[PDB]
Image (cartoon, rainbow, N blue to C red; front, side, top):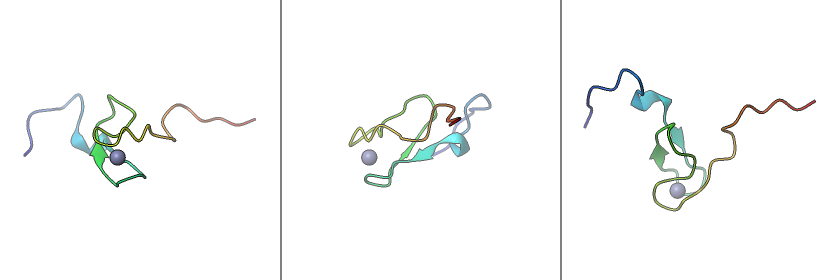
Length: 46
Ligand SMILES: [Zn+2]
């Protein structure tokens, strides 16, 4: 199922490393197990 989403395409989604679920960029944790993403915010070590 795909709908009009030019502002937020499903391609921008992410893959929860816990269960391997797909989620949008809006949230951070998987919408099932709540596997709060790890690599989201701008990670700039140094
Ligand atoms: Zn998950």
